[PDB]
Image (cartoon, coloured by chain):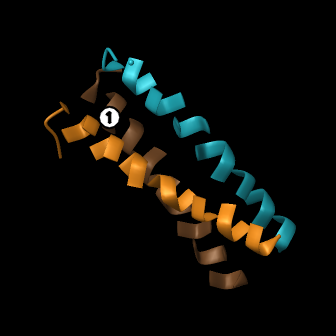
Chain colours: A brown, B orange, C cyan
Amino acid sequence: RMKXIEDKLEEXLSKXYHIENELARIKKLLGER
Amino acid sequence: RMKXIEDKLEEXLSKXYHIENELARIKKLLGER
Amino acid sequence: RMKXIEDKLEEXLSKXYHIENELARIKKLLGER
């Protein structure tokens, strides 16, 4: 259970580079310049 | 605390349906890749 | 290990108010309620 918590935080840290690229894709389509 | 980490990670995971609806509403208004 | 798990949950909580500010910047770039 501790490793399978750690693996599912890591998948947290990884989705959170992906969304934190997606938000700055979208804001920079919405013309923030 | 491990279970009240697991359920309150699961509640992390449940948002990633809603955010990944909203990011793909927005980018797909923007007509986009 | 568990305390430094709990701190990186708390960072879950901080990013999931931050992203839910970013999505509501994006709505107010979309002209939207």
Q: Residue at x 67, y 43 (%)?
A: C14
Q: Which image quarter: residue C17?
A: top right
Q: In the figure, is residue A9 to the left or right of C24?
A: right
Residue closest to the far top: C31
Q: Which image quarter: residue C16?
A: top right
Between C8 and C17, the one lying in front of the other is C17
Q: Answer whether residue A33 is visible to the viewer in this image.
A: no
Residue labelled with disc 1? A26
Q: In the figure, is residue A8 to the left or right of A23?
A: right
Q: Is residue A15 above or below residue A32?
A: below
Q: Residue at x 19, y 40 (%)?
A: B28
Q: Quadrant of the C terminus of chain A?
A: top left
Q: Which image quarter: residue B7?
A: bottom right
- Say what secondary structure mark 1 lies in: helix
Residue closest to the far right: C3
* Amino acid at pointer 1: Ile
Output the chain of dot 1.
Answer: A
Residue A9, x across and y down, in percent: 62, 66
Q: Answer whether residue A14 is visible to the viewer in this image.
A: yes
Q: In the figure, is residue A33 to the left or right of A9?
A: left
Q: Is residue A10 above or below residue B12?
A: below
Q: Is residue A4 above or below residue A33?
A: below
Q: Quadrant of the N terminus of chain A?
A: bottom right
Q: Residue at x 41, y 46 (%)?
A: B19
Between B9 and A23, the one lying in front of the other is B9
Residue closest to the far left: B31
Residue C7, x across and y down, in percent: 79, 57
Q: Is residue C25 above or below residue A20?
A: above
Dot 1 crowding, Cα within 10 Å, few <14, some 14–19, many 20+: some
Residue C26, x across and y down, in percent: 39, 26
Q: Residue at x 59, y 36 (%)?
A: C18
